[PDB]
Image (cartoon, rainbow, N blue to C red):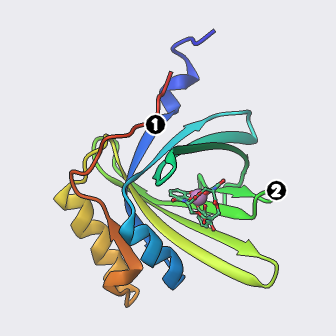
């Protein structure tokens, strides 16, 4: 158990960037703090993810299971949850940017996010995430960033 095998392909990721299509999310997220994300391979076609966010009520965490969906190569779709995530770009030794979308009966929501190899936002990741954001005619309130405001973190093992 807990062998150093596939585990190398999984771990924890710190989301130091955020983007929301709905004003409310932007308003709420812009006022909150950086979030967490840890993913674990449930199966060959199934995957599990643990979320950690600092909520006024305390560190709010949650773990959800998704299904493999190699849309744009290592993308994931959670039909049961109505949430899709697609890794846009990621550095083996640097920052990474992943795109996410969720659709509800009659409504489509998109949420862009950026994660750092550790709980620390980098200028490079910032400029990169923004460069793409600007290419889509994004607006400041549409994006959300968290500076050296870290404190609550999610465990890995
Ligand atoms: O519409 C979406 N959320 C709702 C509904 O989802 C939820 O309320 C919870 N959520 C999941 O259970 C979830 C289970 C499985 C998958 C999830 O993503 C869940 O979040 C908790 O998330 C939160 O409280 C907040 N959330 C993050 O800060 C976030 C930060 C980093 C990473 C996150 O995922 C976050 O949600 C706000 O989220 C919401 O209001 C939604 C859309 C697009 C992309 C999303 O991520 C959404 O969740
Ligand atoms: Ga979510």
Q: Quadrant of the N terminus?
A: top right
For residue 68, above or below residue 47: below
Q: Secondary structure at mark 1?
A: strand
Residue 109 x/y as whole percent: 63, 77
State the image coordinates of residue 145 (x, y, percent, origin top left): 31, 65
Picture coordinates of residue 54, whole percent (x, y) = 44, 50
Q: Residue furthest front?
A: 57
Distance from mark 1 CB to nearest ligand 1 atom below 8 Å: no
Instruction: Pick the residue in front: 153 or 43.
Output: 153
Instruction: Sort mark 2 into few (<14), some (14-19) or many (20+) by Cα contacts within 10 Å.
Output: few
Q: Are marks 1 and 2 in contact (CB under 8 Å)?
A: no
Q: Which residue is mark 1?
A: 12
**In this view, 41 is above or below 90:** above
Give the mark, 1 or 2, whose residue is nearer the N terminus.
1
Residue to which mark 2 is pinned: 80
* Residue 21, visible in the rendered structure: no
Q: Which residue is found at the position 75% from the left and 64% from the top?
A: 82
Label 1, label 2: how many angstroms apart (C-alpha)?
A: 23 Å
| Ligand 1 lies in quarter | bottom right
Query: Which residue is most to the left?
Result: 123
Query: Residue at left 65%, top 34%?
Result: 41
SS for tag 2? Answer: loop
């Amino acid at each position: 158990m807990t062998v150093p095998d596939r585990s190398e392909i999984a771990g924890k990721w710190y989301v130091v960037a955020l983007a929301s299509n709905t004003e409310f999310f932007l308003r709420e997220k812009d006022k909150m703090k950086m979030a967490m994300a840890r993913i674990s391979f449930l199966g060959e076609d199934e995957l599990k993810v643990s979320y950690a966010v600092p909520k006024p009520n305390g560190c709010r965490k949650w773990e959800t299971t998704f299904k493999k969906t190699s849309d744009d190569g290592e993308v994931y779709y959670s039909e049961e949850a109505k949430k899709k995530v697609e890794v846009l770009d990621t550095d083996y030794k640097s920052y990474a940017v992943i795109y996410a979308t969720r659709v509800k009966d009659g409504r489509t929501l998109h949420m862009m996010r950026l994660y750092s190899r550790s709980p620390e936002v980098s200028p490079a990741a910032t400029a990169i995430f923004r460069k793409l954001a600007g290419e889509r005619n994004y607006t400041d309130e549409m994006v959300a960033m968290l500076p050296r405001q870290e404190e609550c973190t999610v465990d890995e093992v």
